[PDB]
Image: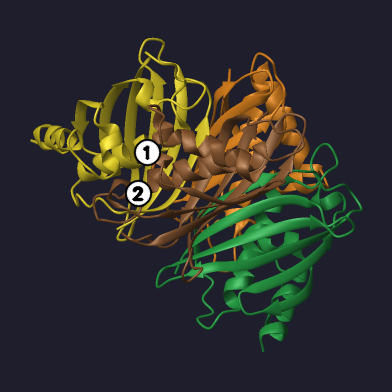
Chain colours: A orange, B green, C yellow, D brown
Amino acid sequence: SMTQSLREVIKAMTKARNFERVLGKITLVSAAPGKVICEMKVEEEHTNAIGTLHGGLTATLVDNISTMALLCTERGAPGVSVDMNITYMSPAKLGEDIVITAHVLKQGKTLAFTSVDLTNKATGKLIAQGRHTKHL
Amino acid sequence: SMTQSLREVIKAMTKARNFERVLGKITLVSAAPGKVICEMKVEEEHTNAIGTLHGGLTATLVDNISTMALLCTERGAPGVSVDMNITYMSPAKLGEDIVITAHVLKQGKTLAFTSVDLTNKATGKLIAQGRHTKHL
Amino acid sequence: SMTQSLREVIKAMTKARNFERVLGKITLVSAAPGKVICEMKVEEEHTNAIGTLHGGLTATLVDNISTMALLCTERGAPGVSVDMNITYMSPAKLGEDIVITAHVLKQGKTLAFTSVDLTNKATGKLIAQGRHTKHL
Amino acid sequence: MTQSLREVIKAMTKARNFERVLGKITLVSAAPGKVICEMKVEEEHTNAIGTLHGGLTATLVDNISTMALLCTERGAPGVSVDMNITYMSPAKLGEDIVITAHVLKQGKTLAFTSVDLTNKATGKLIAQGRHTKHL
């Protein structure tokens, strides 16, 4: 139900023309209260000058999937970005399968906080970690 | 040729297939040692669900133009992202002209640090500010 | 051994003249590879002007306890700060017992990344969360 | 305004809470949304290797950032939401540092600050922090 709702949201992105189109290749794995797990295969359209996952796209995945985890919350408010931090620990090479897990850490009347981990699906090793503060 | 090189990098993005394709609409204003200034007009392809500049694209702009500022130094190495923080203070609306100003704060043997400001060209008011730590 | 060694390191803090003296009240709960848990009861010396745990002390707790986790590693290199980001979600009040948990997220040849959570011991509620990048 | 804020700092020298760690700072100037303080590095400010402790730099960013906020029309201190600090070069023992805070933007409920520590003699950046407070 909630999962189906989100899957529809992700389905829409594909055909969309705004910046959300960039997440067209992601696939939904799970959706639970305040926790969303997506997956994606790195393709050329996802790479930087040197052939690995572009930090800007990692940032984009942190931003949107974080909002998704927020949507799967009781209040369901998406919110507006305030601050975002991203630590890059290991490159994600072309053809690599990545797992994106978003956690709503806490949310109050006006502020929501989330944490997103990207990991190498095959190794479980951390690729990057983002923290997102949103204004509700 | 500092200015000409960046001139070439931009033209490339216009037809690139990787993620940098999303920046093809940016134009170079000036290149100097440790400081690059680009401009861009927010259009539908750069917006979020609510019609304003997408936070992930702002992160993408910070990442790349920050890298351009480092290409304009005696070492000229782009480096790999280690950390990126972004503060969103005011939205950029569709049709709005934005200025992306990037400058090198400090670069050592293996670590370089940059700061990048997006501003409304008209008002000069701050849109977002990002700090970038890169490994060389 | 890892625990005995850490207990000393902490004991030396109760007599220190440098900034580490500010943590003389923390106690060691457990030490494990890449993971250190400490506790501390909030006293006046730990509070800001309004009577809650000072944001600067939280930041100091993150820096040092993150360093202890890094010591409980094969390389055992403490490292020097490069980046730190802290998100404050709920106040820690005077008299409150807090738990400081630190995890080594990843460590390379020259860069180490940690995560440190402060939580209310009684309710397990998250107080603040820090991400630490260190140069080795 | 400067003289006023100067009193707030005199307290820290006497206070028993965590603000006491800032007793050695001195005020240079205070203006709307901008405060400049200075501090000589001494043993009480150092880490295990003998340089300015990262946690104190964090405390300095937090507090002085707040000062700039108190110097605005609204004058509200706000409570911390997020803080980020990039450490670029060590502040050595005996070294004189300058802490410069600027209020970047402030709305109805959220305020944004930026604080630079620099070496007074060389003007070299020691560390830079951004602070997001909830008003």
Q: Position of residue B54 (x, y in %)?
A: 75, 46
* Rendering coords of residue D63 (x, y %): 52, 39
In-image side of D81 versus C26 (left or right)? right
Q: Which mark is residue D53?
A: 2
Circle 2 chain: D
Vertical placement of C33 versus B119: above or below?
above
Task: Say which amino acid is labelled 1.
Answer: Thr
Q: Residues within 10 Å of mark 1 (few under 14, many from 20)?
A: many
Q: What chain letter is assigned to the residue under label 1?
A: C
**Any mark on residue C60, and which?**
1
User: Where residue B14 sits: x, y (%)?
Assistant: 78, 69
The quadrant in which residue B40 appears is bottom right
Q: Residue furthest bottom?
A: B1
Quarter holding the N terminus of chain C?
top left
Between A81 and C120, the one nearer to me in the picture:
C120
At which x and y percent is residue A89?
43, 51
Q: Secondary structure at mark 1?
A: helix
Give B17 or D85, whichever is nearer the viewer.
Answer: D85
